[PDB]
Image (cartoon, rainbow, N blue to C red; front, side):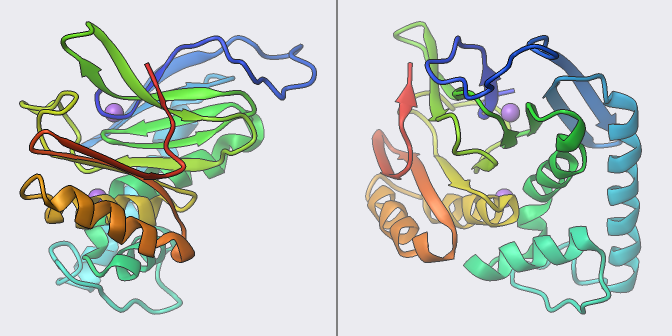
Length: 249
Ligand code: NA
Ligand code: NA
């Protein structure tokens, strides 16, 4: 789904120094209730991946029973050391940009699923709605939005060697207004998907009019020291880009 879909290219860089074993990439869907993943891997992992997602989901359900204000908080929430990993990572990402833990759920799940299986699939792309986690040794292009006029896809380049990384977008579907120029969208790049996902929410919230685009790229630049690597912001015909954001068309 757009935004954040792997788009197939032949790479200019491909630091896999062997390419025996695995050039064959498989693509499958992991669906567990309302968590819906699209995965590109070197092995067939749908089954163990659904079991793992099921488990992360159970932990959140249990944590929500214990901390009733967690699910709908619009502000940072304190969590103890004994809390589940998924809960702690979302809470931390949300606290860095001053939003609620659930603003980081989808990014957190994509990165954790990816971390759990990268050992058996060193090429691995986990797409969770508008959030995407990538491990890779070649150039990869992550599609953001189509250009209706051009007739084709606009994406962000993740150069070989720079993954693992998150690309997290402020909207999950398109959209209905969502295309190049048209419709509000923030996309955030960071190693920590909890931060990228919470930031995409914070930046999304701040995009109300054209003039807000500059407030987002400026704010993203302020957040470089806590992990923010780049931002793409679109609103009201204005497009602003900060940091490590090279577009491929
Ligand atoms: Na997507
Ligand atoms: Na978010």
